[PDB]
Length: 19
DNA sequence: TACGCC
Ligand SMILES: [Zn+2]
Image (cartoon, rainbow, N blue to C red; front, side):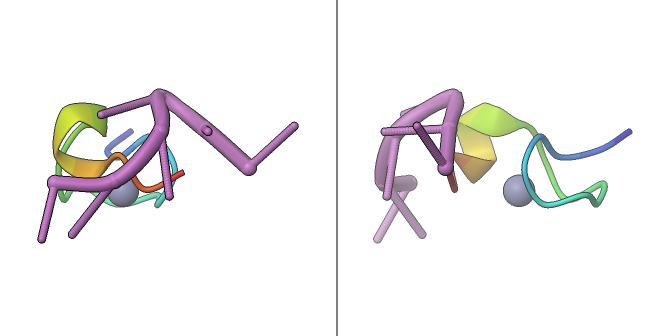
């Protein structure tokens, strides 16, 4: 629960995008 | 911000 690729409550994919 | 992708 958090990011998509990172693993932290920083943001979601539209704010990450980080592959 | 960058693949929402590996
Ligand atoms: Zn992330």
